[PDB]
Length: 117
Image (cartoon, rainbow, N blue to C red):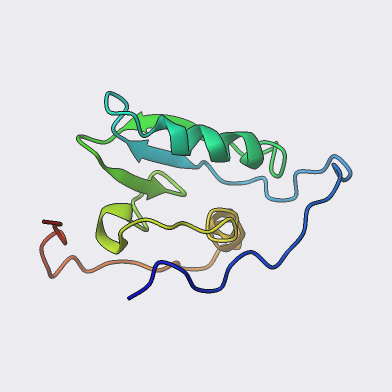
């Protein structure tokens, strides 16, 4: 298939009021520090703080070229399975579904880790 699909439709804008309604979650981007994946964790760490300054997003270790996302310290969506290509709405809707107080998407882990040759 193609990497493209549903490009950016929204436009830019100035810094809105200062409110952290998304407070109530602890994001934890698990990635291989000693690899060079920070380029992605820093590109969002500057946009996540301007959105939800109330939450708490820290950096943790993964293992090797990994990017296990943990909206609440628990892997809910791996990047080594899909192939990457995240979404600004997928990284922001994490706390919106977690802080909601309702069950979130879980994995049964009935299959091995989708490798890549």
